[PDB]
Length: 369
Image 1 (cartoon, rainbow, N blue to C red):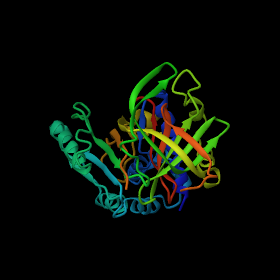
Image 2 (image 1 turned 120 degrees about the horizontal axis):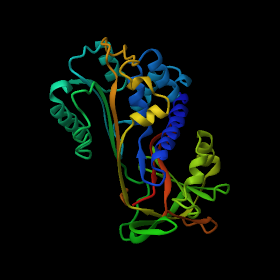
Image 3 (image 1 turned 30 degrees about the horizontal axis):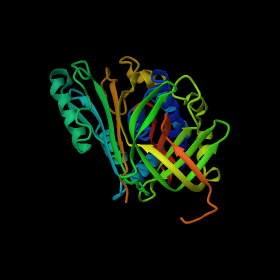
């Protein structure tokens, strides 16, 4: 019920830090859940060591009835009909000279509502590539028009996973456009850049981590189904973004400790937040390999028996992309209420959590406007 929730966040943090190895100071925005589910889907088509590696990496050994639990969660989360826009393009494209097992085809669209669609990589990879881009573009209401660049798919391509999502939701408590001001966002100790600063004074769940001189703010979205949690250091206190310490500490245990009910008080908060857009694209092959998924990409060692009978199959590409817009958009007279500031004018970590299950749908670092 909530084993999967724990599994998926462990992996979220595993992935975040793997990606941080290659970009310690820049914007990162991923959708850990989408990836976890997409790979859970890839999972049921994999056997042998290829399945095992995939399972320890994503921490699936820890979850009973993985797929049953995933079908349930997705269902919960794509609920007709939320206030927020959440649009996922999750598909698996394979070269059309391969006989994909009908029951697998059936599993994916029943357990994950996704399809293995066949295309001509061998002879028509440029059209194939344009066909893939078209479909995601459709699925994302034009928000992600060109997922794959030219060259990303050739005549040697066997199997491709695509996974793009767009999210925009209305705040429970909206910002006023008249309050949003041109203000300096510090990238680090030595560098500033002007951004559009949203301002708001209202009641929010608020926490402090005295150990890391860091603040926690929960901003729920309209409907209460989803919430943004933001981690903001008191000041930049290192030679980079100021997020190094907090990143070193990231575990599921710490994440819960910081964000659980017992450690948040509803308080009056002066919230300055940048209006920002993050669309980040990732071919996850090399990162998943660092994390333990080796065989799946190796044409020899790959064991994808669960989806096809052919012998030279393997994943050529795994492309993930998340897009969010954050703006002012949205729908206490106590004297003794504690006042507190939350001024995100320097880099911060943040995530968008599904409040019911505790699952992390989106995870990112905003460091460089």
